[PDB]
Image (tube, rainbow, N blue to C red):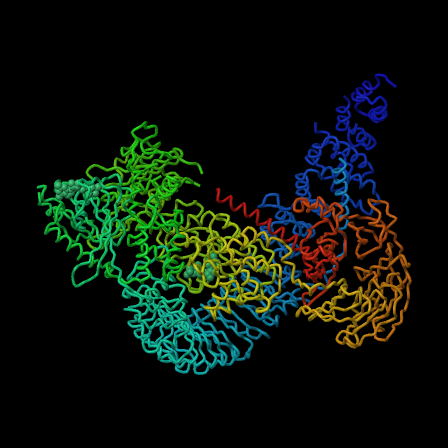
């Protein structure tokens, strides 16, 4: 057995190459076994290539391969060269199967070469029906290991769609292999429609995962070609809402519509298709089996037809008699707006006889057809942007009465349509705005006009008989016309709007309308507003009269006659004062008297108008300072009411003495106050500010004892960083010389005066000489020569007192100070004696008394102490008065309190400010003469009981920390990386003198902004007056401070590299340098028109033509360059060369922002001028236009937004980028505009207020989900939206299964966070937001979301009910008492979101779910399907139920009883939900059934009980009851079949008793007492109880009936004989016995049989023909996979409860397992086993069945239990039978919705890539 034959034989078969191999292969094959020999592979591989094509050796070679990659290259090339020659593929696939199981990666090599080319042919060469089961098993075992790698699956699928092969592509889809992965721009469907594939190949790709964007691209592709079966399949997945009967073809750019496409979109009753793709499912099952083996041991015609944006240049293609010309006749909605049609085809407009919302606007019509009106039942005919000819006369041969809303907006009309009165009788909303109507109108004999309109026409006037024949007009509104009077308006008008006309007085035809409700006459030029005794109408609510010329506001005559008025707009008028009689209009809500410039006072009466929630105060001055951080137009009412209580004059002023390093300040203050003592013989230099107070009872006729508090500020320069905090605008400043250095010190005093002009422009100053004893008195020259009136504040006197002892000059100084104080008069208001409520004075008195009762070590007071001291006294202040009270007392120098939220010490109140000011200056004077270990100025924590904490918890909040004062005045030498005059940008800030606390606060605002260029911090070396922070030679910034020679001013040089990151630096630094100047120093950037516009702040820009070595930088004032905005480049008088403005000031042009949002004005196809393109927003500011070839909405800004604010909003708006957020596209200048995405379907509120019929209980869910996603993104980005209303939800499409539906407008947060409606709209407002007491939170956005959900659910019921009653529309919901959605409004109960509402409607803020949860609770797919739960009365046990489908109008679900051992039928309606009880049997009833008789029109209802007493009772009559034959054993199942075997309609009844005896009856024989059983079929035994029944899935088998009996299922037919006796206990796969060795419980008839037994946690799947257990599907095989982490106690529940308590099978989609536990299972019976388990809604799913209710057919009822162990210790449980009603369409949603999230999650990331780059 051992010789050297092996080597000789191998080598001789090698050399013997022409024709020897036939025997050599046989020899080596024979020898490969015996010694188990081990260099032949290469040669036996070589012989194949050296001599192919010989079958007899090919088979042998394949047989010997099984005993480098080129191997594979020969293998398939062999099997492909012999595709189907013989069973040599067997040997081949054996070879592959052998090779893969030892070399896994080689599989990837096989698919590398060609393996698909042969394996697909093998699996598709009709191997099925060729009984080669062993061979196919071999191929499947091979493939299972081939498709191990998922990437191999994806590439195999890619190459399997290249060659059209439906069966294998389906098999691969069932095996995973997602179909949206190829290229994302040319992914599967794109080429599959390019390569001219089959309809079945496209349908399978669409049905599974295929991204919608790719589907749209493929639709464009398949439009390119002419295909009629692939187009109709793309539309059927892109645009069809079967639940709503719609076609949402809106956004698509279909070039032309042809009926051969929409043919199959319309429903077709004939559509019925067989099951031939079962081959693919079987192969998938085999592959899955082999994979897990390799894994484990090793009517209703659709109505809405939307064709909006498809640029249909013609629609004639549907007018013909084509395939769909019979489905169109019941359309009832047709949208053709925004196309480019013309001449609607006459044949079409009579083809469809049921159309009622035909709207086709923005088309290019040129003649109103006048044959559109011959349709049968038409309404809302809408042609509203076409170019309708000059006249639109309606032909009088049409008598169409049904028209209701005949819109004709924005045409080119020249007349009212002529023959309305003879054609459109019942017309209601005749709208004719935007036309060019010129001549006087017709008498207009319309009998039913309800809302006319004539806006923007050119009307001369109205004929006196214009409205004399329209007795129901309600809303005549002729805006923007040239109108002079009104012609006897009918007495029925309610709302009348007449703005922008030319009146001179309200025509008396308006003053007498007996029901008028609102009257808007803005922009008129009227003179006299008649008093309320001229209006004759008890119901005036709105009186809009802005922009008129009104003198008086007459209310003295009779004010209560306007007691209901709720809106009164009087802005832009010549008003003088508000009469006190305004205090009677209690129902006032929104008063507006702004922009009057001549009002100057508010009467104390207005404090009684507590309903006011807004009150603009723009451009008018009052007797008090408003808008501190409060004064929200509501606290003002509290102030005006408390001042009504008791108004006293307030005498207290501020006299801020100011000096410089030494003067008569303290020795002049201690002489003004006449302080005799000055006990310190030599007082030393001042620390801090040293507030003192001194009363002055002026001993004169004016007994006003004024108390002005002196703050003798610090002289020495060291304290100069904090002073601008103690320089308010209400003061009387002094200043002092020390005239010893006369005419030289007076120069050095210049900065001080400048700062006084910087902080308080309108504050008086008094110079005071301080020296006559020390000698130069000609100083009055220079103060009159230089110092007086050139950029320095309003000097009003000057004196020369000695200031060491009393003097006549000192007395004159006293008199001057007193007379200057009492005559202050800012805005002509006389500050010194203004009126305040006495409550403030009382609080001031008690605080002053408290100042002697405070700990010296810590003079602070806690807010608790203050709220205790208000209780100690009898103060009339609430928690809403103090927020203004303490601020006002801060203004008077009593106590400093800081309301700044960032400064987290607002809880502290610093009574005795003379200690806070003294302590804040201790650090600035403590030095360290030890070791200068750190550079001069930087320091760490180096100093009592916890006071060290608060000291620097104030000081660095005070931005003293590193002390920016006494910090290296001399600048360290710095050199920029590039200084070549052309890579840098430079901007100046020339100002006459740096203000006091400028650099200290400037270097502290630039400093802490670390995330520049977005978190990489820069290196910075910052002296007193510079920073120079740099990241690289590519990004740096030097905010220097130099003085150029021969320039006594002081500049602020900024240098930033001209790179792209540089412009970001420059913009973000100029913002922080400009916002400061207008926040603290409003005097500087105050253009003084008196004199000239110096502005004291000449922000230059430096630009140079000569790139590098320009030898000089050319100045340009920033304002004048901003005037050069009409262009984009600058150029000198020499125009050949020029500089780009985007390079010398990239902040003015919006270039610092991410460059992708640059305007690109060239591609903007936009027309601001027209108002028909204003369509977005009623007379708003957001238009509609085209850009980049797509429709987008521009937002033209008015003159309000300063460009700096626009940039401040764009910076935050530009990096949100979420699929549920309105995203920017471009923004720019010329004009100052903004472009965003066009929300096609407009705001939500419109949709839910006039189009309720589209919200469909699954769009009302997608909208809420998308809005919750928006909030969850915002709240994660740490910004609260603060105002969310159905006015701010912008829809995109009404097709439910879309990727982007709802999108909240995010411009609100920009407009909010830029300029700080922050309190939110009244109705849509959280409880903490209306009261305004508490600082706000995310829990207010959550409450706003709750209200949004409530409005969506009721579909605009609350909004409509509140627009007539707003003052309750807010206050009823301000407490969470808004009513139950179901009782007040008709709505689908939807009771899983009602709990969401009542959780988001909790008053406690942090008790409301956070936004992430309220999105993750809507993400669940079992709230979009649950429809209503009915907790039955307390402790009722019910175990049986039957529905009613014969009366499908309103149905009642008849239940049984288990709580009584004796029988009782338990009726239960659904629309009333009223349970009733009626004992009818003497023994507990077990089941019921419905036998409806087509004759006599009744539905007898039958009931089988445990006693066998088979009861029958009539539907309506509960008295005509006759029990039939008393049965022998317990009846267990009743059933009503479909057995029409007698050539007529026929039915029977089955009585399943506990023994098997089939007591069958007939449909009609139920009436006679003791019915007659036709065929008494005793089937089972006494020990084998008949326990279940079922019926066939199809009707082609003549409804073969199947019933379970004992443990053996049986069946019969019209023969009524047992056709099979299948036995289940005799199973050959015992995992356990009693799961099959028990009585049957359920049976379902389908392609297979699914069966369960008592307490069987596994279901058995038999076949009808083979009678084999083809399936064994275990329940805990699914439950114990989700109950792994969420149930840790389940580890103790190994003896698990949980089993199949009932079956219920859907038609062909899935199967619903009802567990004996508290769970339910979805089973996709075709491919994948578990779809979802929906638990935690009951505890025991007892009964389940299918039914139909009220045209909402096919619902699934689930009678489960919820036991309460309230007294479980008493061995009793509290039972609630929680009957629920799921919508049977659940198994789709749960797999549809879980796709929908994924599609957005990807979009949630891809969008955030644009934020990166
Ligand atoms: N991108 C858009 N697409 C379609 N409609 C829009 C878009 N943006 C805004 N609108 C609509 O235009 C209307 C006016 O917008 P606007 O921002 O003026 O509303 P507003 O903020 O309530 O009014 P205001 O700014 O005067 O307070 C709104 O009804 C909004 O629905
Ligand atoms: N001899 C004399 N001394 C004066 C006169 N006016 C002010 N002084 C001196 O100025 C000092 C007051 O210091 P002061 O300016 O209040 O300190 P500062 O507030 O920190 O700048 C006193 O010590 C006086 O000696 C004056 O008219 N005559």
Q: Nearer the viewer, residue 658 or 633?
A: 658
Q: Is residue 1465 left or right of residue 1148?
A: right
The residue under the point 90% across, 69% down is 1574
The image shows residue 1326 at horizontal and vertical percentages of 48, 59
Look at the picture and state if 191 lies above or below 433: above
Q: How many marks?
A: 0
Asked if one can make out residue 553 in the rendered structure from this viewpoint, the answer is yes
The image shows residue 1107 at horizontal and vertical percentages of 31, 36
Q: Is residue 699 left or right of residue 1077?
A: left
Ligand 2 falls in quadrant: top left
Q: Nearer the viewer, residue 848 or 237?
A: 848
Q: Nearer the viewer, residue 1401 or 1091?
A: 1401
The image shows residue 1692 at horizontal and vertical percentages of 72, 44
The image shows residue 469 at horizontal and vertical percentages of 45, 83
* Residue 1072 image-quadrant placement: top left
Look at the picture and state if 1749 lies above or below 1218: below
Asked if one can make out residue 1137 in the rendered structure from this viewpoint, the answer is no
């Amino acid at each position: 057995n051992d010789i050297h034959k092996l080597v000789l034989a191998a080598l001789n078969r090698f050399i013997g190459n022409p024709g020897i191999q036939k025997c050599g292969l046989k020899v080596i094959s024979s020898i490969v076994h015996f010694p188990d020999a081990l260099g032949a592979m290469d040669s036996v591989l070589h012989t194949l290539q050296m001599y192919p094509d010989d079958q007899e050796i090919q088979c042998l070679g394949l047989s010997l391969i099984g005993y480098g990659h080129l191997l594979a290259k020969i293998l398939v090339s062999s099997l492909y060269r012999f595709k189907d020659v013989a069973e040599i593929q067997t040997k081949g696939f054996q070879t592959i199967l052998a090779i893969l199981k030892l070399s896994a990666s080689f599989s990837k090599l096989l698919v590398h070469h060609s393996f698909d080319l042969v394996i697909f042919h093998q699996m598709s060469s009709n191997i099925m029906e060729q009984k080669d089961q062993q061979f196919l098993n071999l191929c499947c075992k091979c493939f299972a290991k081939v498709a191990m790698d998922d990437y191999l699956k994806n590439v195999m699928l890619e190459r399997a769609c290249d060659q059209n092969n439906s069966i294998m592509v389906e098999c691969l889809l069932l095996l995973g292999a997602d179909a949206n992965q190829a290229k994302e721009g040319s992914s599967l469907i794109c080429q599959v429609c390019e390569k001219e594939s089959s309809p079945k190949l496209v349908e399978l790709l669409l049905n599974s995962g295929s991204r919608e964007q790719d589907v749209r691209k493929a639709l464009t592709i398949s439009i390119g070609k002419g295909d009629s079966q692939i187009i109709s399949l793309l539309l059927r997945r892109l645009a069809l809402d079967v639940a709503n009967n719609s076609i949402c073809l809106g956004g698509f750019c279909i070039g032309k519509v042809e009926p051969s496409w929409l043919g199959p979109l319309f429903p077709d009753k004939t559509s019925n298709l067989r099951k031939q793709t079962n081959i693919a499912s079987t192969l998938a099952r085999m592959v899955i089996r082999y994979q897990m083996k390799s894994a484990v041991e090793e009517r209703e015609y659709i109505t809405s037809l939307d064709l909006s944006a498809n640029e249909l240049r013609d629609i004639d293609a549907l007018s013909q008699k084509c395939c769909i010309s019979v489905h169109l006749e019941h359309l009832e909605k047709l949208e053709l707006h925004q196309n480019a049609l013309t001449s609607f085809p006459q044949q079409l407009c009579e083809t469809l006889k049921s159309l009622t919302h035909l709207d086709l606007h923005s088309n290019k019509f040129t003649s109103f057809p006048s044959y559109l009106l011959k349709m049968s039942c038409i309404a809302n005919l809408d042609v509203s942007r076409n170019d309708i000819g000059p006249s639109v006369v309606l032909d009088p041969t049409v008598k169409c009465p049904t028209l209701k809303q005949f819109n004709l907006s924005y045409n080119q009309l020249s007349f009212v349509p002529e023959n309305l009165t003879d054609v459109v009788e019942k017309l209601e909303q005749l709208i004719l705005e935007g036309n060019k109507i010129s001549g006087i109108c017709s008498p207009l004999r319309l009998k039913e006009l309800k809302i006319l309109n004539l806006s923007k026409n050119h009307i001369s006037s109205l004929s006196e008989n214009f409205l004399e024949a329209c007795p129901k007009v309600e809303s005549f509104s002729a805006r923007m016309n040239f109108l002079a009077a009104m012609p006897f308006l009918p007495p029925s008008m309610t709302i009348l709007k007449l703005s922008q006309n030319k009146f001179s007085c309200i025509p008396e035809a308006i003053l007498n309308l007996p029901h008028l409700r609102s009257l808007d006459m803005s922009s008129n030029d009227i003179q006299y507003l008649p008093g309320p005794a001229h209006w004759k109408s008890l119901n005036l609510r709105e009186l809009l009269f802005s922009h008129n010329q009104i003198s008086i506001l007459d209310l003295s005559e009779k004010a209560y006659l306007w007691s209901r008025v709720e809106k009164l707009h009087l802005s832009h008028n010549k008003l003088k004062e508000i009469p006190p009689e305004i205090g009677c209009l209690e129902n006032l809500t929104s008063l507006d008297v702004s922009y009057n410039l001549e009002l100057r006072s508010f009467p104390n009466e207005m404090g009684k108008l507590s309903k006011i929630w807004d009150l603009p105060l723009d451009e008018l001055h009052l007797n008090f300072d408003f808008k501190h951080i409060g004064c929200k137009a509501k606290d003002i009412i509290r102030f005006l009411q408390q001042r009504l209580k008791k108004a006293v004059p307030y005498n207290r002023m501020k006299l801020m003495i100011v000096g410089n390093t030494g003067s008569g300040k303290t020795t002049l203050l201690q002489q003004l106050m006449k302080t005799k003592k000055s006990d310190l013989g030599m007082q030393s230099a001042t620390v801090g500010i040293d507030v003192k107070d001194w009363p002055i009872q002026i001993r004169d006729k004016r007994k006003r004892d004024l108390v002005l508090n002196v703050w003798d500020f610090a002289g020495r320069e060291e304290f100069y960083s904090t002073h601008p905090h103690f320089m308010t605008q209400r003061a009387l400043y002094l200043a002092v010389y020390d005239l010893s250095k006369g005419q030289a010190e007076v120069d050095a005093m210049k900065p001080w005066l400048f700062n006084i002009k910087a902080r308080a422009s309108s504050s008086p100053v008094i110079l005071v000489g301080t020296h006559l004893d020390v000698s130069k008195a000609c100083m009055s020259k220079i103060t009159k020569e230089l110092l007086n009136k050139r950029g320095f504040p309003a000097i009003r006197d000057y004196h020369f007192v000695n200031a060491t002892e009393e003097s006549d000059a000192l007395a004159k100084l006293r008199k001057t100070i007193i007379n200057e104080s009492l005559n202050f008069k800012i805005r002509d208001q006389l500050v010194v004696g203004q009126l305040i409520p006495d409550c403030y004075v009382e609080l001031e008195k008690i605080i002053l008394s408290e100042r002697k009762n405070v700990p010296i070590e810590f003079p602070v007071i806690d807010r608790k102490r203050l709220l205790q001291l208000v209780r100690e006294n009898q103060l009339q202040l609430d928690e809403n008065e103090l927020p203004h009270a303490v601020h006002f007392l801060n203004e008077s120098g009593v106590l400093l309190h800081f309301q700044d939220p960032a400064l987290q010490l607002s809880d502290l109140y610093f009574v005795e400010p003379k200690w806070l000011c003294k302590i804040m200056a201790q650090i600035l004077t403590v030095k360290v003469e030890g070791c200068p270990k750190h550079p001069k100025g930087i320091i760490s924590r180096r100093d009592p009981k916890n006071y060290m904490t608060q000291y620097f918890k104030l000081l660095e909040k005070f931005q003293i920390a590193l002390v920016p004062s006494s910090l290296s005045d001399h600048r360290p030498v710095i050199e920029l990386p590039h200084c070549e005059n052309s890579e840098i940008i430079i901007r100046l800030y020339e100002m006459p003198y740096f203000p006091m606390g400028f650099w200290s606060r400037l270097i502290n605002r630039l400093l802490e902004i670390s995330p520049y260029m977005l978190a990489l911090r820069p290196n910075r070396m910052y002296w007193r007056q510079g920073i120079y922070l740099n990241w690289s030679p590519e990004a740096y910034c030097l905010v220097g401070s130099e003085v150029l020679d021969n320039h006594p001013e002081s500049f602020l040089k900024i240098t930033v590299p001209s790179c792209r990151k540089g412009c970001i630096l420059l913009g973000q630094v100029v913002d922080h340098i400009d916002s400061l100047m207008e926040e603290w120093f409003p005097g500087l950037l105050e253009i003084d028109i008196c004199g000239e516009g110096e502005t004291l702040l000449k922000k230059w820009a430096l630009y140079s033509f000569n790139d590098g070595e320009e030898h000089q930088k050319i100045l340009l004032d920033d304002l004048m360059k901003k005037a050069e905005e009409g262009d984009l480049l600058v150029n000198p008088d020499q125009p050949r060369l020029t500089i780009p403005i985007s390079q010398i000031a990239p902040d003015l042009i919006l270039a610092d922002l991410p460059r992708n949002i640059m305007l690109n004005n060239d591609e903007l196809e936009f027309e601001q001028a027209p108002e028909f393109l204003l369509g977005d927003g009623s007379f708003g500011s957001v238009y509609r236009a085209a850009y980049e070839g797509e429709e987008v909405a521009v937002k033209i800004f008015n003159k309000h937004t300063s460009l700096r604010l626009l940039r401040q909003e764009l910076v935050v708006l530009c990096h949100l980028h979420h699929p549920s957020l309105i995203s920017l596209l471009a923004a720019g200048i010329r004009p100052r505009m903004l472009v965003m995405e066009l929300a096609s379907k407009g705001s939500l509120d419109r949709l839910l207020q006039q189009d309720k019929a589209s919200l469909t209980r699954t769009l009302q869910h997608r909208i809420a989900l998308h809005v919750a996603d928006g909030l969850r993104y915002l709240h994660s980005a740490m910004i609260i939206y603060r105002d969310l209303k159905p006015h701010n939800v912008l829809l995109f499409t009404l097709y439910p299964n879309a990727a982007i539906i709802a999108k909240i407008a995010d411009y609100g947060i920009a407009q909010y966070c830029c300029r700080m409606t922050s309190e939110g709209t009244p109705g849509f407002r959280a409880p903490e937001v209306a009261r305004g007491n508490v600082i706000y939170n995310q829990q207010a956005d959550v409450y706003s979301f709750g209200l949004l959900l409530y409005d969506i659910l009721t579909t605009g019921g609350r909004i409509v009910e509140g627009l007539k009653f707003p003052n309750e529309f807010d206050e009823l919901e301000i407490q969470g008492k808004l009513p139950d959605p179901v009782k007040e409004y008709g709505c689908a109960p939807w009771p899983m979101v009602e709990k969401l509402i009542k959780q988001c409607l909790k008053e406690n803020p942090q008790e409301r779910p956070t936004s992430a949860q309220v999105f993750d609770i809507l993400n669940s797919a079992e709230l979009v399907c649950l429809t209503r739960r009915i907790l039955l009365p307390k402790n009722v046990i019910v175990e049986c139920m039957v529905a009613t489908h014969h009366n499908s109008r309103n149905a009642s679900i008849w239940l049984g009883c288990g709580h009584t051992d004796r029988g009782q039928l338990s009726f239960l309606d659904l629309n009333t939900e009223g349970y009733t009880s009626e004992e009818v049997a003497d023994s507990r009833i077990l089941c019921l059934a419905l036998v409806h008789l087509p004759v006599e029109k009744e539905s007898w209802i039958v009931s089988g009980t445990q006693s066998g007493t088979l009861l029958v009772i009539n539907t309506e009559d509960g008295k005509k009851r006759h029990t039939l034959e008393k049965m022998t054993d317990s009846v267990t199942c009743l059933y009503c079949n479909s057995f029409s075997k007698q050539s007529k309609q026929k039915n029977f009844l089955l009585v399943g008793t506990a023994d098997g005896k089939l007591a069958i009856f007939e449909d009609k024989t139920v009436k006679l007492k003791g019915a007659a059983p036709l065929k008494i079929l005793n089937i089972g035994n006494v020990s084998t109880p008949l326990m279940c029944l079922s019926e066939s899935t199809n009707s082609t088998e003549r409804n073969v009936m199947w019933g379970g009996c004992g443990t053996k299922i049986f069946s019969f037919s019209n023969d009524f004989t047992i056709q099979k006796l299948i036995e289940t206990r005799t199973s050959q796969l015992f995992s356990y016995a009693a799961f099959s060795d028990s009585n049957i419980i359920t049976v379902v008839v389908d392609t297979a049989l699914y069966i369960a037994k008592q307490n069987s946690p596994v279901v058995e799947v038999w076949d009808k023909k083979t009678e084999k257990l083809c399936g064994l599907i275990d329940c805990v095989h699914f439950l114990r996979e989700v109950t792994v982490k969420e149930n840790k106690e389940s580890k103790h529940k190994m003896s698990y409860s949980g089993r199949v308590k009932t079956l219920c099978l859907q038609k062909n989609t899935a199967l619903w397992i009802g567990t004996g536990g508290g769970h339910i299972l979805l089973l996709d019976l075709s491919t994948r086993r578990l779809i979802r388990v929906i638990y935690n809604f009951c505890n025991s799913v007892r009964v389940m069945m299918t039914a139909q209710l009220g045209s909402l057919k096919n619902v699934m009822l689930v009678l489960g239990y919820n036991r309460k162990n309230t007294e479980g210790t008493q061995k009793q449980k509290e039972i609630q039978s929680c009957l629920t009603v799921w919508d049977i369409n659940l198994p789709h949603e749960v797999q549809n919705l879980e796709k929908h999230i994924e599609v957005r999650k990807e979009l949630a990331e891809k969008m955030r890539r644009t934020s990166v780059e």
